[PDB]
Image: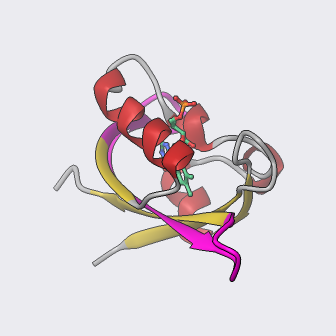
Amino acid sequence: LRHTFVVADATLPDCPLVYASEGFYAMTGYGPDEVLGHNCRFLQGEGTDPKEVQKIRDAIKKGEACSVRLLNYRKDGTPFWNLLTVTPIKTPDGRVSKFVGVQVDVTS
Ligand SMILES: *[C@@]12=NC3=[C]C([C])=C([C])[C]=C3N([C][C]([O])[C]([O])[C]([O])[C]OP([O])([O])=O)C1=NC(=O)[N]C2=O
């Protein structure tokens, strides 16, 4: 299947993105100059379910893995359905260093 991949830096408090695959930009229409160093939430919009967004917010705070189905928006405003799976990467001392996300456009 067609998927995308990003890396969030958990040492910084708001989990900014530090790496995105070629597909992530092409899927969403944002360039690296407007993605890197920002929280992934810029992809959200009016129809994003705040109950689902809360599920990721909690999991990141707890440091667990999570999977949600969010409504996102490209740079041109058009919506797409992003199945998102976040995964915590821990150092050997249990501390969370990075979060990693796989995004799949499941508008079908
Ligand atoms: C986003 N992908 C994504 C990828 C990673 C690795 C992480 C950690 C988060 C995301 N998000 C969610 C966003 O960063 C944030 O965690 C949530 O908005 C909830 O937190 P807040 O503080 O806003 O309540 C992704 N969100 C998307 O909408 N699309 C993704 O591709």
Q: Is residue 55 left or right of residue 4?
A: left
The quadrant of the image that shows the C terminus is bottom left
Foreground pick, 16 / 21: 16
- Residue at x 39%, y 71% (from the top left corner): 3
Locate residue 85, reporting x and y percent. Answer: 38, 60
Look at the image and name its color scheme: secondary structure
Q: Is residue 104 above or below residue 78?
A: below
Q: Is residue 79 visible?
A: no
The reply to whether the magenta stretch includes residue 12 is no
Residue 15 picture location, percent across and down: 69, 47
In this view of the protein, which residue sits in the foreground, 75 or 106? 106
Q: Which residues are magenta?
A: 70-97
Is residue 98 among what the camera can see? yes
Can you name the residue that lies furthest to the top here? 46
From the image, which quarter does the N terminus lie in? bottom left
Total marks shown come to: 0
Q: Is residue 32 above or below residue 102?
A: above
Vertical side of 82 occupied by 7: above or below: below
Quadrant of the image occupied by residue 90: bottom right
Q: Is residue 11 left or right of residue 21?
A: right
Percent of width and height locating residue 65: 41, 61
Image side of residue 48 versus residue 69, left or right: right
The residue at the point 44 percent across, 58 percent down is 64
Q: Main secondary structure of the magenta part?
A: strand
**Residue shown at 44% from the left, 47% from the top:** 59
- Place residue 103 in its image quadrant: bottom left
Q: Quadrant of residue 46?
A: top left
Q: Is residue 96 magenta?
A: yes
